[PDB]
Image (cartoon, rainbow over all chains, first blue to last red):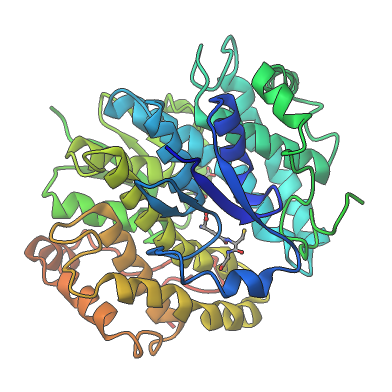
Length: 218
Length: 218
Ligand SMILES: N[C@@H](CCC(=O)N[C@@H](CS)C(=O)NCC(=O)O)C(=O)O
Ligand SMILES: N[C@@H](CCC(=O)N[C@@H](CS)C(=O)NCC(=O)O)C(=O)O
């Protein structure tokens, strides 16, 4: 019926992989976007949406009123029969999921820290071990789960996008990941989306983050 | 056939909710437990298990070779038809999941920090907002998803166990959560497990954590 609603800060943050999945699926959706100066506007609306666990992002479509970014992206995947056709494949996809989140949360965890520049050294020292596993995973695979796209592909894409801002050379040792990122960008729906006015380029985290914050790239 | 293997540090950490679920299900499993001084022993074995994304915990049963704690607990749930009977219920359970992880990771995220005692003030200031949602969730509900146990019940239980160590009064304002914790402890399988030699009481995080570390409680 009506367009489902994806609500979130006007930032990449937790919801960027979900946006990419929806666009890949060419699904109609509309967003409720909260701006940098709309914190009080959100807090005044937060507990008045029928949400069991009020938070950003939320996703409302007439069947569900969801929070939790990973519940939301998995629901959208589930509704298109992409979560896995059996327990073994579902676990495989949840494993891909978590491994990507080790990278993405690894960033988010330190981005608001006052000592970011110190913590970032540790994260960047450990990052190649995490990347290596995906590089190996993509040996003779088009996407993370073989010949067909799954939602962790867009999670990985988002993670790669973000860590490149932390160190533009961090993928130099990982040619298959560099190719993967280009391959996602070569999905016509995704190419179209990234060139559209719907695409949010910045910020990566909340505007007040030490890394990936501010109104514009450094 | 043979007992599945759950591999992890001899700590509560990421895998405690999974142990509780298995025991609730009265499932046979054996553990491969890595001790405080077995870091090199693990690193020598890490890449020799056929794991796609080598890590702790792992779970091996002859059908799967999994890493990622959330993939593992969901696989075990899935194998007992507990993940949800439709996309709406599956999303509900993933939402419960993520909300619990906001508490549990909220702890894990700061526990190894040098400035834990400062960061802990912020976390404990925000914690009541998170707890309030579960307190509300349990109004006239036996478990988080109604009349029947689901894996986020054991995740919440574990989260409550851990935050009580950070502040033994943090549940004083939340009687239904205090009751919930007692209700889980009153599941006979769980009561039996917590009294058994299989139960690991400490540490909460890795032994070297600032919070929830060491060989014994403070
Ligand atoms: N685990 C939650 C975390 C949500 C979260 O931390 N949201 C932040 C933005 S990244 C927020 O501003 N929430 C608004 C609020 O707390 O009211 C998720 O994955 O959605
Ligand atoms: N997201 C992963 C995190 C795993 C993780 O951080 N494991 C730590 C212990 S809590 C570890 O020691 N892994 C061993 C290794 O890196 O080889 C999960 O949920 O399993």
